[PDB]
Amino acid sequence: LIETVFVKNIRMLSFEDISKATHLPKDNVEHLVMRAISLGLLKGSIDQVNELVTISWVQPRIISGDQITKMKDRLVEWNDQVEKLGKKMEARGQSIWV
Amino acid sequence: LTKSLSIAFENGDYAACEKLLPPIKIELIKNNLLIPDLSIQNDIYLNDLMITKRILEVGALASIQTFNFDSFENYFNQLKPYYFSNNHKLSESDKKSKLISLYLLNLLSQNNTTKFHSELQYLDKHIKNLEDDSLLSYPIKLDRWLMEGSYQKAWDLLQSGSQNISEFDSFTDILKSAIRDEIAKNTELSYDFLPLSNIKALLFFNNEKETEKFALERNWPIVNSKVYFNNQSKEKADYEDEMMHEEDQKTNIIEKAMDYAISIEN
């Protein structure tokens, strides 16, 4: 449960996605989320009526070659968003950099 | 050549008229020089003027009927100076009323209403109460019924002009093709589902097969006998996003403030 949220760009999971992955009924999928937050492994708020768990905190956990690469990719993608914008702004208001 | 075009028109042959016309174009240069081109108009340049109107008049009516709309607009444009001026002295005739009626349909069947209404002024000055509307009412009624949006009144006016197989009918079928396209532009917003019997009804088909055939050509996805306008809307929106307009089409949050900033420092 903690693993899935962390590796996805989004910080929300459907309960149907939890149902498959931990192989549990839909009753216990909800209880698993409650228990996790009580443990303080994940933090957020629970929608039972959009059937989402929306996370704001992940507890720091192991690093592994696998995980090292997963975080690297996200930074390149976000690096692209920064880089191209600053060029939009440079081309704009050219007369004024004083 | 010159008098030969007249009687070829009269017989009912219009493939004959166009064949023979490129020879007479050379002699149309000769005729044009005889008149001063309407700087003053004698009864001698009146005699000349009739020769000049005659070649072009019979050429232009014939063009329609061989389905050379392109050639029709050329001949008609040539009449215009004689039509403009010297009214009530060999400028206005029965053929003129017929010829302008047909042209107004040309502009309308091309679907330029910019041009059609600007051409209508020019005619305001000429005949519309000096030879009243009796054949020119036809294109004007039609344009109005689609502006209010009534395609019922419009199809009827076309269908009863189809009774009259003359040359007015050659623009009527174009105009029935046009009513279909307009509706097919509208239906995207109007609905999301129509059964196939319902699509047929709006598009003025009497055959359910014929409806399916237009849909291929008009790119409507009918799946299990029901249409999906939401898909079509997407494709056309996608094309409009693709083209370079796009920073200030959307207008970026950042872009707004950058404008403000340099103005106060300039």
Image: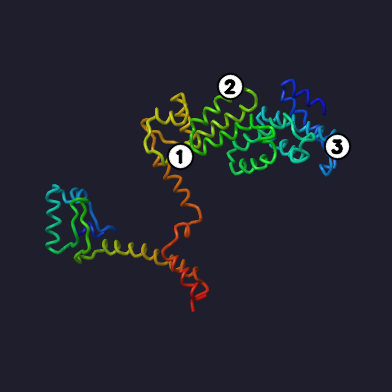
Q: Is residue B265 above or below residue A82?
A: below
Q: Which residue is mark 1?
A: B186
Percent x, y for residue A76?
36, 64
Kindly identify the amino acid type of the residue bearing the numbered disc 3. Tyr
Chain of the residue displaying label 3: B
Say which residue appears at 61% left-offset and 42% top-offset. B117
State which tag comes first along the sequence, 2 or 1. 2
Which image quarter is the N terminus of chain B in? top right
- Contact between labelled residues 3 and 2, with CB atoms less than 8 Å apart: no
- In the displayed orientation, state which residue is furthest to the bottom: A98
Say which residue appears at 56% left-offset and 32% top-offset. B175
How busy is the neighbourhood of tag 2: few (under 14 within 10 Å), some, or many (20 plus)? few
| Label 3 SS | helix
| Label 1 SS | helix
Q: Which residue is mark 3?
A: B45
- Contact between labelled residues 1 and 2, with CB atoms less than 8 Å apart: no
Kindly identify the amino acid type of the residue bearing the numbered disc 2. Gln
Q: Which residue is mark 2?
A: B163
Q: CA distance from mark 2 to mark 1?
A: 29 Å
